[PDB]
Image (cartoon, rainbow, N blue to C red; front, side, top):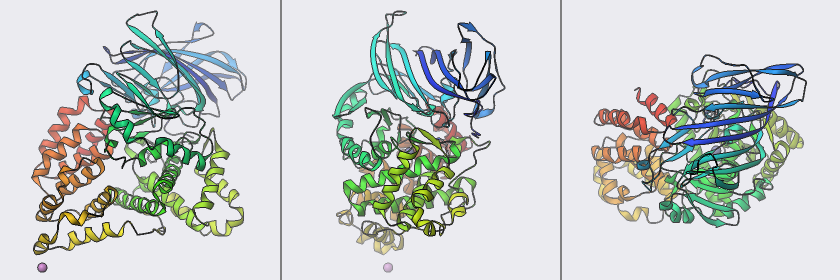
Length: 606
Ligand SMILES: Nc1ccccc1OCc1cccnc1
Ligand SMILES: [Yb+3]
Ligand SMILES: [Zn+2]
């Protein structure tokens, strides 16, 4: 059972297909049209069914060419309002019908951000983007908003003719709109059954440039050249992923580089990955995020978590594949470096939440919990740590990669639970059951806190990071002079980042140390978002007032929650910036992403 959804479950009825016909109204900030759901009964004598909705206005529901009865239940907070539809004729098991629903979205749709021209790069046109994961599809259209159901889709999207629509689907042509010549209709087909959280739409002044045999990069014209360079490893990564995961089944792999308020590093929307412009470091150094989104083309999009309680399946295996891709490109030592960095991030999350907190369990119980509130690094890094531990228990990366490929093959086009995964692990490694039985399953899967066992990590790339961090931590005032720019000479951007991560784990440091750090290392000059993020957190937590306008600027000039949330929290926790932090949030709140605005609000207790 999916406790995040109010719809009839998959055991009752299944959506097989969505035909979406809609128009994007920028003057009203509404999407208006029809969602025609092809629904298959899983039961005898089915006479009603329920769909998820959230902030939707329903005009009518048509089945067999006539309007039918429906009712909207009371809103259940973040879950939205259940919509019960009265079938005109009782259905037998496996019978299919088409239910056509006329709806309009609200300007406040938690799935959508509507941007004014001023919020864009070009300053001439408005822009719209969606983000359905986890349970925001119901805020665009009535559906069974649960990843336990997979459907294909087709769509026709009418937009102002000077703008471009793109979806998580194959582009299927464009024509002028016969109902309004100031508009174009863009068409889309997704022939691979997907969970509805992977439905995606962007509308904006978009341009494209090809960067590989199956990849266009899309963005506003101002960002096209930089993006094309930043993401040029994309085809190489696809070829590696295909080798590890089996065939890429989605046809194209395009990239869309969003405006700065996109709330995540990326979103694995099929055919069209969405990414933050905060990846544009200029040197490809944040490309692990592309590797990660590419990996979702197998783990997540082919094999899918049945409910959000099992989100680690999606994320753990994806981080696992992600790190293999980068290990193939840059070496096994770098894979170990990133793996160990991940353990560090998990230490951070568990410390932040508290070692007994329910959100530090690998498998979580989301009953009455908003998934956006529960979201963290835990499913990513605790999930990865389990897989990395298993890899080491079961004979190493070659062997475990054989399991991963078989697992993808076994569960493609399906939605699964942790028990499904574990059953298959035991099946695949049947001659190593003795070794599998040594695993503390109850702790790994169901207990809060750090895992019961830490994997073995190569230290080669990490040692210099730890060494330098420890010099700074143990330094007294008379040691500060010995620091110099040459300390960084042999460190990659990755290692600088890990140096800062190490030091941040011990923050605050004395203000004089941090001032010295800026003096000799000039971290203020670094535009790498990951590095700049940790550096500003270190400065604010160490009470450097000079850093306040810098942290405020970063927190607001982009909206990636990974960065915006902790910067606002740090600013709020520093007495000198507290008031300005709260004021800045209040002033920006209406023009922020609705999920981000909600969460920063909660973080700031505002
Ligand atoms: N959020 C979350 C936390 C712990 C386990 C599963 C989860 O899934 C819900 C989710 C996923 C992605 C984005 N937003 C919410
Ligand atoms: Yb000394
Ligand atoms: Zn992911």
